Amino acid sequence: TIKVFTTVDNINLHTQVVDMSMTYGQQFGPTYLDGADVTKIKPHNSHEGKTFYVLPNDDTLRVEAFEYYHTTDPSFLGRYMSALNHTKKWKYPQVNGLTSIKWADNNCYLATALLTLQQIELKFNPPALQDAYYRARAGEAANFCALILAYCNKTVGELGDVRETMSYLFQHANLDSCKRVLNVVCKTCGQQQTTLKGVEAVMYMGTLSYEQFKKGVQIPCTCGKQATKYLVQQESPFVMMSAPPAQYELKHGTFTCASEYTGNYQCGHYKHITSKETLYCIDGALLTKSSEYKGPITDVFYKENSYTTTI
Ligand SMILES: CCn1ccc(-c2cc(-c3cnn(C)c3)cc([C@@H](C)NC(=O)c3cc(OCCN(C)C)ccc3C)c2)n1
Ligand SMILES: [Cl-]
Ligand SMILES: [Cl-]
Ligand SMILES: [Zn+2]
Ligand SMILES: [Zn+2]
Ligand SMILES: [Zn+2]
Ligand SMILES: [Zn+2]
Ligand SMILES: [Zn+2]
Ligand SMILES: [Zn+2]
């Protein structure tokens, strides 16, 4: 009989005492210590006085779990601890003043997303996600990477798409004040104006150029003809312009950061391009430098505050 603590958020700690013969699974349910499954393991001396993550089994823990993670999915904690057991072993070097990830288990898309998040203004709604966001920007990104995999329903080693990962994260972020007003002009139908909010207001799939998005882009109308969609008003701290991988010239000072993707569909490699005093390329732990750049780009991130068109 030795005393321990059980928690679901590492904030509210509940005091318990455990028997040595019975395993943790017989007494608490699925139990984790430092991200390691100890459901079948039995108590030792070092376990006394230490805190254990446990699956919610009563209503008090069920409520605390939602208030930290904003999910009731019973599998979330297990998927989170499974990813964390890998991400704790990864290395997170500082590259060009930013926290990156040494390559491991196909994490190239995580590194590009992690580098992008440190360069755009974002506030997460789940307290677990925002707290780990802060710890990650300071250099301790293991818990943050595990949460990203858990919220995106992705496992370690699985092949990830950066645009898809950013979209999942934006749905758990406060983008309520973000607003986008578009205008589509068809020769026959006429002029239609639409207003988008939230995640739909910051993401566009179709073109990398924020300038071309303002000047107008060609989309098919309901009548079948090719109408023209252009941006009327944009109120958001950033925008994300995505397009299928293609050769693109990035000029210093015209953008914030970008995602480079080489190789075949789903089984390629991501790289991160950021515009500082010059153009920097971050590939995990490796860093290169160039005055101008041209390569296969699929995401470009631009700064914004409030924009209104002249048309
Ligand atoms: C509308 C047309 N479009 C939209 C996206 C793309 C696209 C095309 C190509 C493309 C084509 N040829 N080559 C040679 C490469 C490549 C990509 C890039 C950005 N990502 C992945 O490769 C990828 C997709 C994944 O999951 C995807 C599964 N998802 C629907 C649940 C998972 C992991 C990765 C790496 C994206 N084209
Ligand atoms: Cl929610
Ligand atoms: Cl949320
Ligand atoms: Zn409590
Ligand atoms: Zn929420
Ligand atoms: Zn691993
Ligand atoms: Zn591992
Ligand atoms: Zn990779
Ligand atoms: Zn029309």
Image: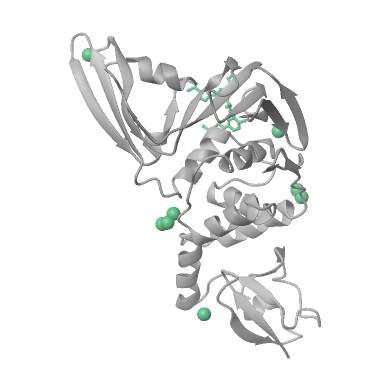
The scheme the figure's colours follow is one colour
- Please give left or right for residue 166 compared with residue 273 in the image: left
Q: Is 176 in front, or is 270?
A: 176
Image location (x, y in percent) of residue 59: 45, 76
Taking the view exactly as shown, the residue that stands out farthest to the bottom is 1
Taking the view exactly as shown, the residue that stands out farthest to the right is 45
**What residue lies at 39% left-to-right and 45% top-to-bottom?**
175
- Please give left or right for residue 167 compared with residue 16 in the image: left
Image location (x, y in percent) of residue 78: 61, 60
Q: Is 301 in front, or is 25?
A: 301
User: Quick check: 295 above or below 62?
Assistant: above
**What residue lies at 69% left-to-right and 28% top-to-bottom?**
280
**What residue lies at 69% left-to-right and 42% top-to-bottom?**
97
Q: Quadrant of residue 82?
A: bottom right
Looking at the image, can residue 75 be seen? no
Looking at the image, can residue 56 be seen? yes
Q: Quadrant of residue 308?
A: top left
Image location (x, y in percent) of residue 213: 40, 20
Image location (x, y in percent) of residue 182: 29, 26
In what quadrant of the picture does the N terminus appear?
Answer: bottom right
In what quadrant of the picture does the C terminus appear?
Answer: top left
**What residue lies at 32% left-to-right and 18% top-to-bottom?**
229
User: Quick check: 140 above or below 63?
Assistant: above
User: Quick check: 16 above or below 231?
Assistant: below
User: Quarter of the picture for ligand 3?
Assistant: bottom left
Count of numbered circles in the view:
0
- Please give left or right for residue 307 compared with residue 162 in the image: left
